[PDB]
Amino acid sequence: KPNILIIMVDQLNGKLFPDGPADFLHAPNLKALAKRSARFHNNYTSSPLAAPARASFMAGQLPSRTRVYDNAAEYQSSIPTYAHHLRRAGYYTALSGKMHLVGPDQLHGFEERLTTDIYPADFGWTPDYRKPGERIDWWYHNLGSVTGAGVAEITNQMEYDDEVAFLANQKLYQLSRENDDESRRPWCLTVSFTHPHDPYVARRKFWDLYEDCEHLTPEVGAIPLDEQDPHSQRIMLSCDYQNFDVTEENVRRSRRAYFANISYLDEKVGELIDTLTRTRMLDDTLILFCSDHGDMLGERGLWFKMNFFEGSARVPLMIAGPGIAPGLHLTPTSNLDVTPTLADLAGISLEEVRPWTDGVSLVPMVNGVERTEPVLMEYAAEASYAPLVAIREGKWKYVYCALDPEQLFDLEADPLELTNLAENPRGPVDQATLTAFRDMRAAHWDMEAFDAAVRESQARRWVVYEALRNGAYYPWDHQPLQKASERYMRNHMNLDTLEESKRYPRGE
Amino acid sequence: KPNILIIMVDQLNGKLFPDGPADFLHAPNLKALAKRSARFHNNYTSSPLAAPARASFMAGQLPSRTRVYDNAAEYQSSIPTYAHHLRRAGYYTALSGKMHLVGPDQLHGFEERLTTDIYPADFGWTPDYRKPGERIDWWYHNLGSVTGAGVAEITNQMEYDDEVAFLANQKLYQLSRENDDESRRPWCLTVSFTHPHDPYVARRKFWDLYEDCEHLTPEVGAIPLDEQDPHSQRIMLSCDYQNFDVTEENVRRSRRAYFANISYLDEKVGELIDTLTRTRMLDDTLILFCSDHGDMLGERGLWFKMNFFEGSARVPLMIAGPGIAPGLHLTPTSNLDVTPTLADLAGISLEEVRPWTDGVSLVPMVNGVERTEPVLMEYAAEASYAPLVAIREGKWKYVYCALDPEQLFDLEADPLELTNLAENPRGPVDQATLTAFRDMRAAHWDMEAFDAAVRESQARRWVVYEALRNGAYYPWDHQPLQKASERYMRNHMNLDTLEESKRYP
Amino acid sequence: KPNILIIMVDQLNGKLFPDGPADFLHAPNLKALAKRSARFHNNYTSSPLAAPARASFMAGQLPSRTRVYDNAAEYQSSIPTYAHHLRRAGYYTALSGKMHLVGPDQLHGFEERLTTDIYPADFGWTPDYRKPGERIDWWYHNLGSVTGAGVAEITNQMEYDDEVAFLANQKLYQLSRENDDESRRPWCLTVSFTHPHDPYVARRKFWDLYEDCEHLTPEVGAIPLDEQDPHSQRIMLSCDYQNFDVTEENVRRSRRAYFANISYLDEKVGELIDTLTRTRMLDDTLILFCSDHGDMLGERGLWFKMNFFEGSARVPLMIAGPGIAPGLHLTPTSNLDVTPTLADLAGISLEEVRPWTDGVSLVPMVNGVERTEPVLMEYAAEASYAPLVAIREGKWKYVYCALDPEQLFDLEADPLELTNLAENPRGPVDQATLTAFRDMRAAHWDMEAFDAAVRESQARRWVVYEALRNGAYYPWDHQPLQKASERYMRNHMNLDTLEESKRYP
Amino acid sequence: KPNILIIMVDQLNGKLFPDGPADFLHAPNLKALAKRSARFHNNYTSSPLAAPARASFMAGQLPSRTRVYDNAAEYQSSIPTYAHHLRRAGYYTALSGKMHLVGPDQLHGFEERLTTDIYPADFGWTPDYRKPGERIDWWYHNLGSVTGAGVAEITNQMEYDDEVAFLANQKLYQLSRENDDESRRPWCLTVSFTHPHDPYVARRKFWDLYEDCEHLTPEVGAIPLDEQDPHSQRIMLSCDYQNFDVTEENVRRSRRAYFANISYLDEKVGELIDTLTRTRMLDDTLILFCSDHGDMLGERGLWFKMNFFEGSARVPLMIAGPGIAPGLHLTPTSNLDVTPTLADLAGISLEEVRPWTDGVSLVPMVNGVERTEPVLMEYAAEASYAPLVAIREGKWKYVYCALDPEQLFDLEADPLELTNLAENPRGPVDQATLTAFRDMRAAHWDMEAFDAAVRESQARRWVVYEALRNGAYYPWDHQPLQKASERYMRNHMNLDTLEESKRYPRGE
Ligand SMILES: C[N+](C)(C)CCO
Ligand SMILES: C[N+](C)(C)CCO
Ligand SMILES: [Mg+2]
Ligand SMILES: [Mg+2]
Ligand SMILES: [Mg+2]
Ligand SMILES: [Mg+2]
């Protein structure tokens, strides 16, 4: 069984990985990793928001099945994740960094978690479909990220990611000490960074890399509120866009700091791979690179995620290591496919994972078997007033919301999604394609039931959360375990025996 | 708003509370409490097993709605409980003792929990409908409790309940120090004991009280396996009955220690009442006495719970205090009614709890209003191979399982449930009644959907639990909060100011 | 090896134990214990203040040797205590309650400590010989305890002692589960209550016992400030006496509540004895009753301790159990003798404890052997401006401070210490006696070296403590160990095996 | 008040810093630091063993005064340290890394401690003068460090120091967030590394730096046991030297890994200085570089410390920052002088520190005032059977032990200490110098009282420690504080307010 290193980042627009990292990015370590990787060019999040995407990523199940509809929805402990599947199959599993799990279980199958979460574990960020049009200023996104972009040497997120990286490398060194033990468990380490999620604020060393950057304005500029589709209008209102004057210079500084933060992350990828190389674990390790959702980065005038346009819904996905053919894949894939792919790579049978996953293993794709299943997406959090669903199949993207006109995009002819073919069909094939996706949408979702489930989940939480914020608060944040009395040299040990056990490689 | 003291005990057969405690029980404090209480004589659990009964009790929802089907089913943190409803209404809420919550949330709305649980918080005790007939010896009930009954001065349970009682009285004293602050929150303290749950082992002082006891033998004796109904057979097999020779003296020793442990609990009830009296909180405090399920106590040859017969499904319920007229009520009620009753007594509107509770407030009954809503029960754990449901309405009890012959009992004519009127109707009224209950059951439950939901829950947990028991174990047991650097006299305080604040009256 | 139960109380005037508890005290359990005890009637503290007395008590060394001169002096972890000596000899050792250890070590050899301390563990209460005459209002004794005496159902101290008692009895029950394992360690449990230390506030049930009490007034009344000896004057000033109008009824209420809190403690003594009896450990258990210092209780107009007069310096001491002949002993003894007495009773050789203890075993006295070693006492805390030492030998008490007139009392002729024979000798024998005590004092103490050592200790702590109270505070208070994932039933265990191991007998 | 960064390392032979780091060392960051520093060439430990040196360093008091005679002697909480003095004067004080404090107080005035200790906090390593000639194999030094030298990518010590460095830099970044607050406290951060203490085992990257090294054998080779002075013989026996065949190749590999570990440390010095530079704190920060004791590194056949020869007793000392003239100082100085120097640099009056320190401030030396006080040293731990004391004054070193012949060395004429002038006086001046040091030794120490105090301390601890190791053990190791429920974003906070507070510099 190979080891598995999952490197996850937050809010990375997948269009920036057209074949590994785009040429204009300063990302030597991810570009070298890409050359060894199977690269999934048209890979999609299952839900364009952090906690829904991550609960879905961990379980290989859509939000409608995990019930994690938004950033404050409880993730049940009894739902199997890839950590459970691998752990059941004999793996040591650990997590360093972010997973935005909501509720008192902060492990969800991981055997060890090295850091707390950057974001809350409670029900505070619960949307309310009963009050459509409201926004909550103390936690909603707003365009102050765009007007406040710039340069700093420490931020909340850089403190977080510096520690995620350090503790992940330390864990790799600790794991190497078992390398000569025949009975060692294989390990699976998830390293989950919060960058390049906003605030768009970068260390000067990486900001300086992009002085001459030619990609600091999006190709598709800002669409006026009156000319926007209804969901994009709800997003603009939820970002408080009327109270911010976003200048061309703000757009450029935001994109520049965001690319700088990709370079910041690239340096950390290089450290992890260096640790794997020096500890002699690299040849036996699969490395997966992934992200939870994208960032519109100013395209169409939109920032952040919460929608199904390419910039928000596309995320990179790369896999390298023993048995993976390097190459670029164009067939659309999904984050839903990661858990069954990890299971397959770990030698777990198809039947063991079948009842628990909605995705498919990508290993047959890597080995030249055509993948035909569509890619599905869902959204049911802030800036929605009712659930949205999307189907990505072939060259098409279809988006449905009971409250909105449908959207249909031909991404081969119209990759910037500038022409809505459900509104303006080019001909008879477009009308037939629309009818096919409507039948497909009825085959996969009951949208009235979906809306009812989301409403009940929100209503429960608002009752419970109001109570939990009265009186003494009981926090659910993960606290990494304390072990000082068993670490380093203690006087129930023999010093020479301890030193030999902690040294690796030995006798060289 | 009144204070609320909830005294809960585990595995207390409600037939032993015919009008408060039975005369033969040595329970002077519970009898004095019962004399000033509204007493609900025909009160039922929602599910005859610890965790399902308690999750249902806390939420006022049936197991099919809470999804807590068995003793290892996760209770979701987002489900509102009476703790949430009261806390939201401005109560300080606390738990001392047992609640058998499964999963990483060990508070479920309680603001403070003073003890860990006596039982596990993880998925270990998950049944498996895919292996009907199996038993898990290391945690199933077995008849060894009956053959091992007797006397001891300490047990696992007595250690637990001694501490539960101590910390509850300590908390009451602590709360009394706020009794002169007009800004004080009203409090709701749940004190949840593990007795008289088995092992049937009692301290000598309480065992000696039942030497001449006339109730050491059940009136309905053991029914041989071949004459038992199918569910009773499944229970006997689950208890490993074939590997135990249960003598008459075994039966007598078990009941004697069980009664003795009721007397053990009665002394602790008196301690709490005493604390309320001397702190001068008694007149402003509602007191509820309740249990999660009963114990067959050898009746029909069965022990423990897991069934809908009276001894297992009946539990006492009493309410006393400000605005509570004392009296005996015979209309059937259930534990499902406690959470809406608590909300009503705390002044919460019916509309605030209507979407979250499926029982009804008993406060109208206390004030003379006739109740007509039937009582529903569910069971889907060990010794079931498919879910069972029951309906209790008027004089009738109806029990359905897709795998078993139906049962119908007329509890006025047949209080010991010796004649199954579904099999042996007395005439056309019994047949019409059976048809009426079948139609009512079909309107309330799809038993095939219920069975699918339970199997899905079991299978899910078996994947997860096998993973969680590999590698380093992460426990979910509640650990009461460590406060030593802030307790008593510390040198950021003024000693005189501290002594005055801690003195009451 | 016998078990050892040490019952310690705080601030108990030893004159109230003339032969066990005084007849007028309602203390049936302590009187029954005293009837089977060796009782040491003329027993003295080593230092009339909490932390110095207790550090001296634990080590069997005087404050000049432990360096614990006052209530804020660090007790070094390397100093052997009776806990170390017994633990080294194979005992499990535990503490429930108070010991007023100062510094980051809150165990000092105890293997387990069941409660935090009621008092601070840091250097806050450090006196300063550089500012003679100052008082620190936020922690000094003051006469407000006398004017504030009365009745309450909870206090800071009653919360503390209720918990001390509960956890001690719980621990005894836990220890009984090992009583049938031949490989068991013998145990030594120290149960250390804060009562009858002030505030003089009692529960109504115990206060009502002293309604017709004839001992509510001390026989020796208040001595006016100008007629007081210099040290007594320093105590009255330290207590802020000028700002309190202490009436006769104040005096009576304080003594009444103090006696009532002795009765409060007596009920807890009976609880412990009951636990030992029902667990069948009583016959194999030594029981020691002791106190750290006394309380003047208004005698001479003084309250509390900090002096060498009988009411402040006398503390009871009793020993009962296997191999202990009951009887009354009048030869002076001291708390310094407890640690070598415990070691001797546990079978530890005299040579193993000789280098670490400066008292003597009382076991020879119990067996009829005359004791001749004198009793020494020291004091160097608040209301002293330089150290004081005392010698107690035969009928005599001698008290020296470089700043004050000497005191010499003949306690046979003058048990209330009303005639200072150093100032008013009766004849040449008194003068020769004074000279003999002066020579003995000079051989035992260099008072100038003692004073330099105390000032150095105070000054050191004042530099350190001012730093430690800047920025984030790091508390040294003991936090009892969190064990919830290993207590009661957990799913790495077999339930039947667990129930059997936790049941005893 | 300037900030103060104290960089401490363990077991660094001071002869390797002849004027900053020796030319042959690969240490660019320490060499650049040295060019800005006042450098104390003839600086001495106060006691050649870890815990005695460190308790003495913290208090500015000799072991005879601190009572910390050996590696298991309790350090009383009531003894003032430089952390107390600075904290009382308004400083935030923190420690990352090792201080080998014995006893339940693991802070000794530090307001925060970021790591546990690498070594035990209990009484286990207590020598026993009642059994002269015994050794305790499970914790005594032995020459297996020399025969086991080599190359590894992780060791006990590298795991420790990697975390010391990471958490120290993180603390600097956190402290920078207060930089614009007028009411900020100044900070004093001690960063205390365990390298280059043995095992002599280094990462390959740094080992490779010394392939051509010309210093891999000591100038003074191994002295046979019969030809050794009595204390050196006791050290050889305590190291179990008879059971090890130390080859020339072992000597070279040990020295090579030790120099590699200096280079490992030099990289961490560079990171700390980079953090100070980017956070804009460097110009207001004093940087002190120091060590607890040396390492003989094979010289005379000896390894490790425990003696007063130059290699064991000399340690580097450098100070750089506002108001310090750079330059090299030859007058002998002591680690005892650090606490009163820090006090002086922080503006604390001489009188405030006078009753609590045995050393003198070095600031007047830096400013051209001649220092005349001698340097004193003491040793009373393993391989001593009675206390040893030493005086270093002018060109002389004098060593006294009641059980041994005296030693007298003229370090100007005889810098390798090859001629004992107390045994072979060159003339009448040598005999007069010996008599002067004897009178000086009687003026500073009562050696019989010293021996009695050490004996009583050992005897107490053996009683107590035997008891503490019966039954359940209560550990004293420092456990760094848990704060997950107050870290990063929690839902009692406003997200925008949090991000602004955690970003620094702001608005750039
Ligand atoms: C990331 N935000 C918290 C700003 C909004 C997502 O719920
Ligand atoms: C460093 N050693 C532990 C090996 C010896 C010093 O006491
Ligand atoms: Mg995200
Ligand atoms: Mg139960
Ligand atoms: Mg006291
Ligand atoms: Mg060292």
Image (cartoon, coloured by chain):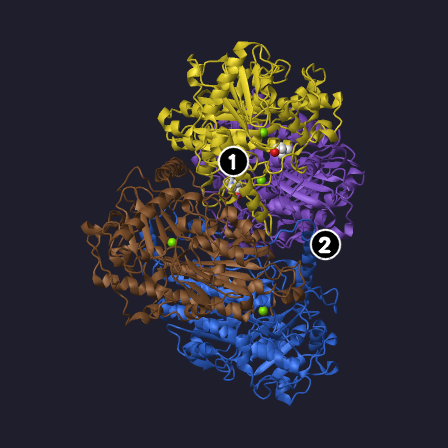
Chain colours: A yellow, B brown, C blue, D purple
Instruction: State the SS at label 2.
Output: helix
Of A360 and C438, the residue lying toward us = A360
Residue assigned mark 1? A452
Q: Is residue B287 above or below residue D174?
A: below
Q: Quadrant of the C terminus of chain B?
A: bottom right
Image quadrant in which you'd find residue D279: top right
Residue C204 figure quarter: bottom right
Residue D8 lies in quadrant? top right
Q: Is residue D131 above or below residue C214?
A: above
Between B321 and A336, the one nearer to me in the picture: B321
| Amino acid under disc 2 | Pro
Q: Which mark is residue D355?
A: 2
Graded by Cα atoms within 10 Å as few (under 14), some (14 to 19) or many (20 or more), the crowding at tag 2 reads few
User: Would you say residue D256 is visible in this rendering?
Assistant: no
Report the quarter where the N terminus of chain B lies: bottom right
Residue B224 visible to the viewer: yes
For the residue pair B43 and D168, the one nearer the viewer reads as B43
Q: Are marks 1 and 2 on the same chain?
A: no
The chain under label 1 reads A
Residue C104 horizontal/vertical position (percent): 58, 54
Q: Cβ of disc 1 within 8 Å of ligand 1?
A: no
Left or right: C145 as drawn, with respect to B50: right
Picture residue at 52% right of the left edge, 16% below the top: A434
Q: Which residue sits furthest front?
A: B428
Quarter of the render that holds ligand 5: bottom right
